[PDB]
Structures are given as C-alpha cells and as structure tokens.
Amino acid sequence: MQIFVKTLTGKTITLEVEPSDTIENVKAKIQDKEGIPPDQQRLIFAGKQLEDGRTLSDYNIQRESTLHLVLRLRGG
Amino acid sequence: MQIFVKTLTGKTITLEVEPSDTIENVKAKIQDKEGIPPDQQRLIFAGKQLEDGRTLSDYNIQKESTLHLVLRLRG
Amino acid sequence: MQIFVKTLTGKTITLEVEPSDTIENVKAKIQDKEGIPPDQQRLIFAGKQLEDGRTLSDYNIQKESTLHLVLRLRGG
Amino acid sequence: MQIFVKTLTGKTITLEVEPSDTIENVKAKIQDKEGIPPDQQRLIFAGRQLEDGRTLSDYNIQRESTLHLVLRLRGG
Image 1 (cartoon, chains in turn red, orange, green, cyan):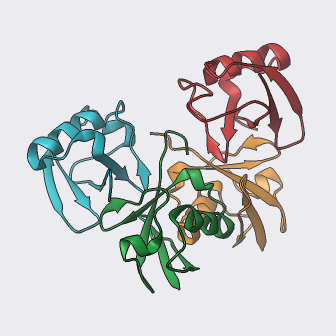
Image 2 (cartoon, helix red, strand yellow; image 1 turned 120 degrees about the horizontal axis):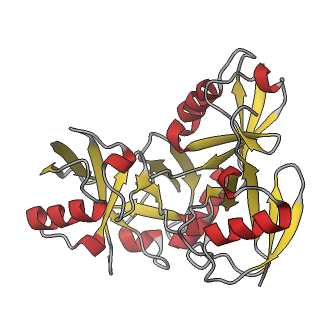
C-alpha cells in the first residue's frame, strides 16, 4: 500500500509499505529513497511521535495515510 | 513578543515570549497553559526538532513566528 | 449543559452538551475545542472509562458534572 | 521503595516496588493487594498511560512518586 511522508517544510515522498511493516522498516525505506539516516528521523502520525518497534497496523495507519517527518540533528 | 505554537491536529495557542527565552522555557509556558509535561513535548521549527538550551533568537525565531508541537510519550 | 472535561495534568475544558449526547459526540466536541482526535481519547467518570455508544444520561452525568480525560498511547 | 497508586475516586494504595519493576509487574502487585485484574487496570503518570513492558525507571518514577489508576469498564 501507498502512504505519503511529509516534512513540515514541504517535502513529500511516497512509499510502498505493508500494514505489518515496523516504523523502523519505514525509516529504512525513507533512507533508501532520501538517504536520511534513520537516527535523524522522527515519524509522526496524528500529532503523536511514533516508536520504531510497532507496526503501521498498531497505529491504525491505512493506505494513502499521511505520515509527518521531522529531522533531529545536534547543533541545527 | 508573541509567537504561535500549533499541533498537527488543528489546535493553536499564542505565547508571550522574549527573544532570550530558551526552548525549555517555552515548554514550561506551554505546560502552564496546556498542562502538557515538558518531557512529553517536542518543539519544531524549519522542519527540525529544537534543543532545550537554545534560545529563540539562536534559531532566528521572531515575533509572529510559528513553532509546531508534537507529543512524545517517551516512556 | 455545561460540563467540565479535565485532564489529570490540570487542564480544564468546559463544554456545552445535552443528556442525549453520546460518548462519541462528546469526543467530537473535544476535538473541535482542543484538536485531540476522538479515537485518541478515553473519558473517565466514577473512576472508570466511559464506553462508546452510551449517552451522558446513561451514567447520570448532569449539569456541571466533571469527566476526566486521558490519552491511550497504544494508538494515540 | 514505596510509590502510591491513586484512583480518581480517592482510593489510595501504597505499593512496595523496585525501579526495574515493569508496569505489568506493578499491575500484578495491585491485583494481589486489591484484587483487580491487570487487563482491567490502566496506570497513569503525568497524564499519560504507561506501557506494560516498560519499567518504572523508564518513566523515571522514583520513590514516593504517585501514579493514577483507572479501571477497565466492561459494561459500566
């Protein structure tokens, strides 16, 4: 299924995922499509920060759902 | 001065701040107004999570600027 | 009816409602007021969570009653 | 160390625990001291529901800290 990942600055990317995928996995896909290290990533759904161990099913994330990406890097 | 803190769900609140206010000071004011504990908060500007010991001016956040608030039940 | 929905952290949210208003409706008004997604909230009264579907009248909730709000983390 | 668990109805209960005790471990202690099944307990600290797999030290709950307990309403 397709889902959208957006930053608060406007960048939007699409990703083929499964309801069984973990947030960690999603982060890895974001790394392949955008080169952003998972460590500097923070996925958000419904204003809540997401934890890596859970799956998209757990958060009730359906197809074409939009996930928000925020970067986290020391100093900037 | 005043700045706005918005959630990704529609809510928006205004805060009276000073360029010299740190991010943690802003979290404390959000707590005073919304009751959200500062450790559960994560403030965002220019697409990135801000750091506690930094001031608003360090990030060039000015009057009427907009910060976004996301929650993190750190656990 | 003006009731009060209070978080355990000191925040009070007043709301106009009616005896026939069901639980999900109260959550809807809560969203409009504070933006918190309805599925994200757990309403409390008489020390216990209020189930989806019953109205305020089914719990004898009346004018100026106080309901506590807490967020369920698993999906909110 | 001691910590206090309080219900919204005013029931206060003292528990003996260790910082490394999991929320689930704490619920077992509540059941043995009060008879409430863990599946029906919802523990809270600073307005947020605690995860069963995490420990008290994870939420930095220390000696004499106070938690909240709301019951799982199956039918009322």
